[PDB]
Amino acid sequence: AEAMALLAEAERKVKNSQSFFSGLFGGSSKIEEACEIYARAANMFKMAKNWSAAGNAFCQAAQLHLQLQSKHDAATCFVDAGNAFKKADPQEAINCLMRAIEIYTDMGRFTIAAKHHISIAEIYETELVDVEKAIAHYEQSADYYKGEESNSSANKCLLKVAGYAAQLEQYQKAIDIYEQVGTSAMDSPLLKYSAKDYFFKAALCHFCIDMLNAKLAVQKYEELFPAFSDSRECKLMKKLLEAHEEQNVDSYTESVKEYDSISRLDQWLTTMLLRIKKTIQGDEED
Amino acid sequence: MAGRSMQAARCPTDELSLSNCAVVSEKDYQSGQHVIVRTSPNHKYIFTLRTHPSVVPGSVAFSLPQRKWAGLSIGQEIEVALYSFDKAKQCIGTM
Amino acid sequence: VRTSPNHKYIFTLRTHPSVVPGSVAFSLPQRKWAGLSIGQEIEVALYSFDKAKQCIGTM
Image (tube, rainbow over the protein chains, first blue to last red):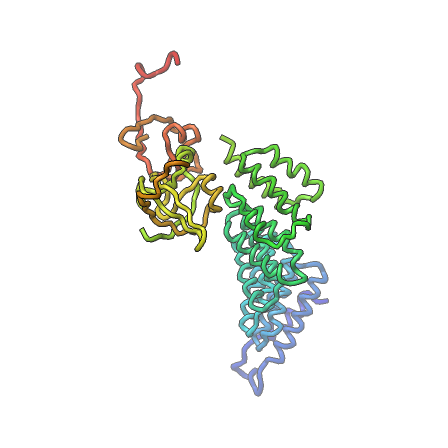
């Protein structure tokens, strides 16, 4: 219960012994008791809905637990310190997880480093928006997930790179990413149906390109075009290529006049719609 | 001469698109010369050069019709080489 | 605007933040009247008119 007395009785109990207090063995029993109690204390603040004070209570517990010698669960206390300000409003969970991930990889490990590097990336994408750094976090983290054949996040965090990167700034990465996912997507008997929208994303990114480079993917890809769900990928394209190439808008726009009913359009698709018609503006708008 | 790495770009303006000539820069080739674009060990195409002070040294600009024949993309690497005709059987008479 | 030894054209200035210091931005008409494309370095110089003779009265 004590929000303060566990602290006050442990702060007078944390001290290095070169004195009459030294004696025979260390005070590692004392700081072990203290850090277990700090863990309970950061629990009682989080139970009391104090995720800032609780999160800082995790921060002392999480930093002081390394002082005996415990890098094992000090990483867990770092994640708990991160989860508190991740749940609470502000930042500084970013530092709890950057203290976490380096120490976790310093154990001789790979996975959870990436599994919270994505957490920092989610914060720096959604919340503490630093997408030019979060996308690097997805990138290096997906490099770790690639080097462990955890193909899930290996494809996923790359998709998070490319879906925002293409629209904002990186163009050859768009098709290079959606082809790297697309080949091994065609490989597995589990994956080759997810490849349809993956090559849709490879195609409909136009990179200031007026061409049928999407049709280069058509006469590349294993569509099996009697599968009509790729006609919402490329017959869409077989209209709009020549709509954009004949600088025409009442066929290009008509494609989504009919395609909005047969497919709900999210923000990224309509932003790419607006992207290719900014290329149409640059073809038409004087 | 023997061939160099070039990068495909877009024709500067609509003025050089009605000439059916590969627009380049004066720092690389020279107006009057002919070239043979190479894209594979089986697709060899031959165009005419025309300099223009807007092309980037080390890149060739093509119009859509030229790009609509050779399957060329805006932003790829291609090997372009000067190609000199022979005035015996290569002079067109009935086309 | 000085581009070549036989093309001296006169334009009106208007500052704007997006433009890069040491770069002049033109519109489609201008760039289709002066025969210019992006990536070519032009020689820009201020020019001042004669108020009595140049001012327009019937155009």
